[PDB]
Length: 179
Image (cartoon, rainbow, N blue to C red; front, side, top):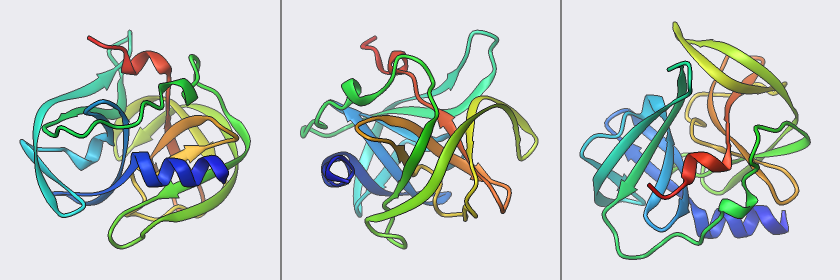
């Protein structure tokens, strides 16, 4: 709410890649995070502004397993308000999460997806993924990249769904360490 709005306004952006429309959380400085399937190229459009992508890291875990998250460093002066303090050290579920979506098609939208549960392994379109969580809410396409928040916590990034359920990549603060 009071946190979600602030987050929406200052850290969540409408984005397009060659793969379509996406929601993008900027975490700090010029570092933003994207669902892997957005596949950022050398450039992206952030709110219709064309922006060079300086670095794109596809996140993987210790077992080398796909986390379905892509860390991008963006070519812009303006820095993101640092929100790392709202991200938990350890991947954590929640009782009453809100999915924040912000694309051109779905502008500034909050979706009460309910309870976010620890799910773990997930076979996203054939490719194995780790550290996923789940929520019982018809999730639709075009909501990929949406930000799952709790009371003052950013806990995940929506990466897909099976019709009846939405799936998110769990967020750990350590993903966003400098170098």
